[PDB]
Every structure is written in C-alpha cells, then in structure tokens.
Amino acid sequence: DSSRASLTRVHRQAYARLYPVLLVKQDGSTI
Amino acid sequence: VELTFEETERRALLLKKWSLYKQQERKMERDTIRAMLEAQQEALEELQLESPKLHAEAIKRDPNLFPFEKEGPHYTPPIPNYQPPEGRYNDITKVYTQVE
Amino acid sequence: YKTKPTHGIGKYKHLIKAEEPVRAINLGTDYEYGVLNIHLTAYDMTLAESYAQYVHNLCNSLSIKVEESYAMPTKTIEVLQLQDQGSKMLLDSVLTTHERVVQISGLSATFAEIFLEIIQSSLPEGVRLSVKEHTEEDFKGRFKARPELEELLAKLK
Amino acid sequence: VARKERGWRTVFPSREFWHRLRVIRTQHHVEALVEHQNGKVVVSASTREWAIKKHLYSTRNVVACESIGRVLAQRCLEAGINFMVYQPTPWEAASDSMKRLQSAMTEGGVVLREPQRIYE
Amino acid sequence: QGIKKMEGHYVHAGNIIATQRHFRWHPGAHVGVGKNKCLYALEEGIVRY
Amino acid sequence: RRTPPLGPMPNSDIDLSNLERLEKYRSFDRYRRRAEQEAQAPHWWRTYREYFGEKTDPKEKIDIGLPPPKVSRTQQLLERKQAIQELRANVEEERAARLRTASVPLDAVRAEWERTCGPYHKQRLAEYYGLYRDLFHGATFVPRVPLHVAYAVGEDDLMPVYCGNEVTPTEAAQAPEVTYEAEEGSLWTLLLTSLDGHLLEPDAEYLHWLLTNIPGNRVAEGQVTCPYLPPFPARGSGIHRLAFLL
Amino acid sequence: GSPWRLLGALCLQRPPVVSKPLTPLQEEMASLLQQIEIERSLYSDHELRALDENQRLAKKKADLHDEEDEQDILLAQDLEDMWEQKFLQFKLGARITEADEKNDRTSLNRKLDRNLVLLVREKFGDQDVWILPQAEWQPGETLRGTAERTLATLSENNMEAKFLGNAPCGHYTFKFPQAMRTESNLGAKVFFFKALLLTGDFSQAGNKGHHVWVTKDELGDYLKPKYLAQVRRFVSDL
RNA sequence: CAGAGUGUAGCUUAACACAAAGCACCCAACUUACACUUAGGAGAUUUCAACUUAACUUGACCGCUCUGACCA
Ligand SMILES: [K+]
C-alpha cells in the first residue's frame, strides 16, 4: 500500500513550518 | 507550550499501538515475499523437469527490464476534461562551479 | 610457536577484508545484475527521504548489498502563470524537486521480479521510482562543473 | 589480605576483585549476578523467577532493572556480601537502567567498590 | 629482547618475564605490564603460557 | 618443522570464500557474548582454567537430601499466565511502569522466593561457603525445609541468621529461637557446629548445640543431647563459620 | 515430444490508480505527526508577516505614524481567505467512480485504489471456465515469449504491458478428466508470468462475456478451487 | 474426499526445575541513511483423556507436508 512509508514528519532540527497542499497536475490528478 | 499530562499520556499510548500495527505490516509484507519466492522457485523446479532448455532461458537476466520507471499513485484520478491554466516553468537552480 | 600444534591460533587477518585507500562499476553476470541505481524523485522532501529509508531497510532484510545511499542536488523550479485578461506571466509558486538514490548491487536475475513488485507497491503518492543501471556519467553528475577545464579544453578542440 | 588476581591489563574486564556484580540483559528478562573471581555465583536475582515476575508489569524495562537491584541488595546482605566491583561498558554505564540498578544496590547497603588489599 | 623466564620457571615478584617491542605475549594473572610492554611477575610462582 | 593440530582449530568453521556475504558482529556486545562462550568450552591446548580453576571431582556430588516436591507444571503455568494478564490489564500498572514509579514489595518477594527458588539458592550459597565440602565431604543436599534461627538481642530486637550474615559472639550468648514448619508426629534433630573454631585439630569441629527427637517444631521439648555453648572464635584467627543443620 | 502439454499464462495486472484510504489508527498517527511537526518547527514567512501585520496595525492605533505600510494593503489572513475561495471552487476527481456503483467488472475505471487482475473466459470441452489469458508454447520461442504472444491474440486489445523478468511466478498442473486422456496427451502445465498494464484497454466491440478485471479478494468467484490456490500465491494484495 | 508422515511464536537437539528460554523481529530518538547504542513493543506449546505426571509418552481431535482420487 502507498501508506507503507507515507506517514512522516520533517526530520530536521531547524526548519520552517510547512503546510499541506494539493498539487493539481496538468491532467487533473492531485497529490 | 508544555503538554498536559493527559496529552502526553495519550501520545505515549498511541505510539505503543503504532509499534504493534507496524509489526503486523512487516509480517504481511514478509509473508508475501516468502509466498512469491516459494511459488517462483517451485515453478522453476517444475520447468526444469519438463524442459531443461526452457529453464536455462528462464533463469537468465532480461536486458530490457531496466530502466524500470513507475510513478506513485495519485490522490484523486485524472479529470477527463480539465483545462490547466497557461503558464511557464523557469528553472532557477543554482549552478555550483569548482574553481582552484 | 611454529613447531607446536597450536601454531596460528592467533591468526585473524584472513577473517577481515583487506583495506585499500574512483570505484570500478561491476557489470552483472548472466544470472545477476550489476550495480543498480534506484532513484526516488518527489516534490516533497519527506516522502522521498522516507521511501529511500524504506528501500534501504528492505534491502537489508533481503540481504541485498547497498553500495551507497546518497541524495542528488535539489532542483528549484519557478511556476509562472498567465494572469487573467493579461499577457504578463506572474510568479505563482516555487516547487522544489528532491531526489534520493539507493545504490544496490548483486541483485539476482530471478529475484529481480519479486524485488521490483514490492518496491513499487509501497511507493507513496507523488513519488516517482526509476531503477537504472549505474554508469560513470551518473557518478560524474554529482560533482561541480569545472569552467576552467572547459575553457582550456575548448582551446584544444 | 587475600590475593586479588592482578594483571590482564590488555584485555577486558579486569580480574582484580574478590566479588563482582554482573548484570545480564536479554530480550525478555533482566538478571543480576554476584560471583566470586573463581567463577562461582554467590547470589542472584532474575526476572525469570516467579517471586519477582509476579509483581512486575514488564520484566524488560527500567523498573525491572531497579527492582532487580533492590532484591539483589537484600540477598547480598543475607549472604554476607557487603562489597563488590561493577564493570560496565561505556554505553551500559551511561544507560538509565544501570544507573537506577546501581542506586538500588547502594541504597540497599551494598558498596560497589572493594577495599584495597593489605600487603603490609 | 625476548622471554627471560620460560614455561615452568620459578619467578620472584618483580622478575621480568619477557621484553618485547610489540605485544607478542600478553599479561595474564599475576603478571604486570611495564610502560614499554615489559612483562613482569607480580607474585612468586611458576610461569605458565 | 610443523606439527598438525591435535583437534579442531579456532575459526575453522568460518567459510572464507563468502567473506563479504557473511554476517559480522557489528557490536562489541555481540562479540563479547560469543567470546565468553568460547572461553568456557573445553580445549585441547593449555588454558588458564587448567592451572587456576579448582579441580572438581569428575563424579557428580551425591545427593543426600529430601526428595524434590512434585508440582503440576501445566496447572502451575496456567495460573501464572492468568496472573500476568490481570496485572497487565490494570491501567494504573502501565502508567507506573511507563513513568518509572512502580516498585516491587520486597517482603512478598522473599516469602515467594523462600517457597520456590530459596532452597536452590541456599544450596548454591552453602556450596560456595564450603559447608558441603567440610560437613559432608562433598555430598550436597537441597535445604528444602526453611529454617529460621534468630538470636534475641535485648527485649525488643532479634538478630536473624540467614546464610553467612555476620553475628557477633555477644549477640549469640544465649541459645537462639528456632522455628521451622513441621507436621505433627514428625521428629527432627538440630545441631550447631563451628567448622573453623577447633583449636587443636584442623579437620575437627566443635559441637556447640545438639537437640534430638524434637517433636514437631517444638524445639523446647527436644532432648538436650549437648547443652548450648556460645561461639568463641579466637582473637586474630579470622572469621569462623557456624552452621545449623536440621 | 512429452506427454504434458506446455502452456504459458499471463498475469496482467493494473496497479492502483489512487492511494489507499488511511485506516483509523493511521489517521490518528497522521494527525499526531502533523501536530508534532508544527510544534517543533520555526515560524514560517507567512506566520511572521501575519504577526508583523497585526503588530503594525496596533502601532497605527497607538500612534498616527504611517510608515507607508505598502505590504499592509493585503493582510496575511486576507490572502488566506482568497486562497480558500479558489479551493472551494475546484471540484476534485471522484476516487469512487461510476463503475464502482454500477459494479461493471469489465472496466479499468472501477476500484481505483486496489490492484486488478485480468481474467478471460475460455471454453474447454463444451464448458466455460475463467482463466488467466494463456497461449500454447511453440518451438523456437522462450516460455515468456509465449506470454508476450497472449496479448496479440486478445480480441481488439490496445494495451502495452511491461514484463518483469523471464522466470515464471507460478504453475498449475492438471490432468484431463478422462475425456481425451491418452499417453500422448496426459494433461497440461501452465506457467504464469506477471506483467504491468502501462497504458491501454480493450475496444468497445466486445466487453462483457470476454474478460473481467477483479481484485484478489473477489478472485475466487471466477476461478476454480485448485486453480485459485495456485493463483493466490503470486498475486499480492499488499 | 482417501493413504502416510507431521506438531513450541520465525529458527533451535531451549526447557533438570527453580522456569515456557536464547536469538531473530517491530516502533521511537541518534544517524544523509545504514550500523551501533538508549528507551519501548508483540508474541507460541492444536485440543482433551490416560502414575493427575508428560511442550516431551500413548490414544483420539485439529492444523500442516507429501502421495493418489477429483480436475480444463
Ligand atoms: K581451627
């Protein structure tokens, strides 16, 4: 399954906050 | 912000469940590789008895296997009639050069 | 002592691989592939890093030698979009592409099918898998471009 | 006044002791031994024992290691063992488990250092 | 440099058993090692390899 | 000149052709564990154990004690697993272990240990102290009947005798209070001997106390075959051993 | 020749089109991971601008000093409002398609999250049976080459399959049920080869009675007990 | 469906009893990652009856592995 290694967090000590967004591709599919 | 006792207790209990859930993911993935490997090896042994020449070709490497490219799944499927906006892509990657 | 039956009880250097102070690529045999590069490209750094970690750990479980695990240089791409009722392109978003490579060797001819099936099923969404054969060009692509050598080489041309 | 086994300076651990505390940690259990330099075990406390296991939620955590120290310290006093050496590795000594086991032994009365031999 | 006391030889405390530039022989029970890797007896007894 | 080994040499079963594919230790702890195992095995070359290890007799030690108790492992294992489930089910137990605030009751541990592993731990400890070597010329027994000896010191205190704990001659001036679990109609003999007290003869002992034909556990009603004598370890002679044998 | 007839089957698989839904525990862990990530992160540029903007709005109230405040024209929350409006206007593709509600087991569009296997119905001895596409081995051809040929024999198919390796991933050995059971023709031996459906699909001429695309769970409805036991070993459902 | 063999969680010729053990394994932190270390997690005798003993012996009962029937 795609969830095998998809539950993650930024493994850095110093990093700015990141926000989840949907990247709409050119065929309409999203990720 | 300091976490409350109830929160730290809820996070500790959730992670304890995560160890067992991931332990069962690996087991399913570890029993699938075994099943596939056994069936393949069993089939290859049966293919050697039937015809040795075909078995020799079966165990050879496939030159056309690589390069092997596969994209991951999408979140939502493609839209049949979706028109993307017009735009341009401008690569702004810094080029590093070694001097001396 | 030499004459005694216990001669050589303290030998140990035949049990260790010799250490030698770039690296020759070993082309695969008829039944085993050569050095293989497993590229993992994703628009999200955490997904590529997480899957590269999964593939490394999976290869350890399967006794597949991992020659090297390294990251390729990140590529930043500006995404301009034509404005409404206008001919000017305005900067919309900046998308970075992060790539991770898990370099393996010694993959078997028969087991290659099973290995590829497992590492594609666990592929996260938005992560691209590309299994290529290692070449000198792949290794050289990791190093800075030398402009001085190009100018001096151009004179010879 | 008894001889301690001096020497073995190039290997680990030392033999220069009369009694030593030796802790064995496995995947499921925690065992602590007090043994004489000649190799004889004097007293022991293990989470494999039902007397200890029945009171422990887990026999493999820090609490189990602290409990083994408290049980062993009492058994040491009943056997007459008041002194012993403990020979941990750098990572073992820094571990929170071993620090709690050592505190349990010292609070229980056992001294984890041995007196110097008298030569004269 | 070499063995000064062979197998079975009686030694006294302090007697140098062997001298070596490298650790050919290692110190055992009741055997000290000097700053220059010199092996000497810490007790009176019989040398054993 | 060379001589063939008298047996299998170390590091011989290692296949040197597949060295790169062989598993390595990777940790100091994994090598040490294997190293300690090899050191204990018998070898055909000269070893430290040969010259310094005590020369134990090859024949096993004759057992002269009471028969082991018969226990149903199946029922015992079932009850033990059930108890662990009940303890682990309690949520307050999990938080105490997770927060490292839990503790065991030492009083209960000793009571259970005295019923279960106590006898074997006492035998192992008695063998270390040399009692079986001296008292029974090497024959060993499992002390399956717990013996509780206590010297009354003052009017409100007791000095318990365990298995090697130090008791001073002043505390042992009078006969101790001896109590053990015994059925009705049984007979017992209790003695006290000083293994090391004897002044003239090295191999002999001193009989400090002898009580015979004790009915049940009523030690006071036994026949005083030998009256009680307090220990008299001589000055400068070291630490002596006094053993109560039931 | 040999008594056993050599056959080459093809296990053509359509890999998941969309990601699989998160389970209840995975959702809890995903929320915790998001919370931890926010907790240990530094302030983002957006957060800083919102803070400064709120601060600069305060000083204007306290003191009439303007300081241009060009960027203050649009606030950080005002931008967030515009971003959400455009999102609510876009309609995402349906992860559950019409074929999932109609239950059309002949279309690829159904069951996007799970893997599908191709099953073609073939008539043996006046009896219809569901089997993986197969062809008979012929001299001068590798055993995999027989599987590559099965696609060409498929009826009005425009599909490009990627074959993984040369070795077979399974086998099923059966004997004819006494019909044409002879020393020359004792039975058959099918060898399965896995392939991935890169792109393409069948035509609209003949769809229903020909083929179906089924997940591994609903794979037994069509295959036989013994034929199923051998197919459920190399068909993964990870 | 029949005939044989077979029986501790993944492996073990671990289990005398004092006890279901050792390793392998899963998560987290450290590590680019791996490894190591620390701190946690999950586990088994197929089920009953026979000196009551018995994970161990004999029987049935279950699961398993092959050999045939059944088979496209
Ligand atoms: K004496």
Image (cartoon, coloured by chain):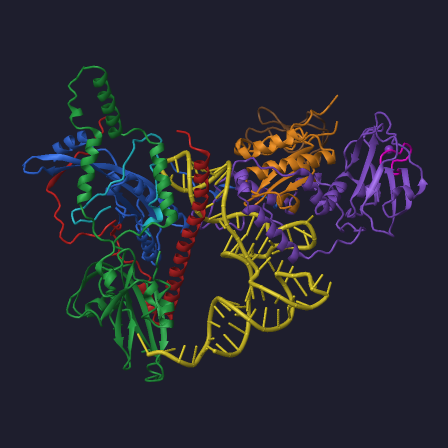
Chain colours: A cyan, B red, C blue, D orange, E brown, F purple, G green, H yellow
Q: Quadrant of residue D24?
A: top right
Relative placement, left or right, of D22 versus F169 is left
Asked if residue G110 shows in the view, the reply is yes
Q: Quadrant of the C terminus of chain D?
A: top right
Residue range corresponding to the magenta coloring: F195-205
Spot the residue most to the front. Answer: G61
Asked if residue C9 shows in the view, the reply is no
Q: Where is residue B52 in the image (x, y as percent from the top left)?
A: 34, 69
The kind of secondary structure the magenta stretch mainly shows is loop
Q: Position of residue G222 (x, y in %)?
A: 31, 70
G148 lies above or below D114: below
H57 lies above or below E6: below
* Identity of the residue drawn at 43% across and 39% down: B11
Number of residue marks: 0
Q: Where is residue G177 in the image (x, y as percent from the top left)?
A: 36, 82
Q: In which quarter of the image is the N terminus of chain D?
A: top right
Instruction: Pick the residue in front: A30 or C59.
Output: A30
H38 lies above or below E37: below
* Identity of the residue drawn at 55% across and 33% down: D89
Find ligand 1 in the image and state its quadrant: top right
* Identity of the residue drawn at 83% across and 45% down: F137
Q: Quadrant of residue G236?
A: bottom left
Task: Check if residue C146 falls in the magenta segment.
Answer: no
Relative placement, left or right, of A6 versus F48 is left
Q: Position of residue G18 (x, y in %)?
A: 26, 52
Instruction: Pick the residue in front: F101 or G190.
Output: F101
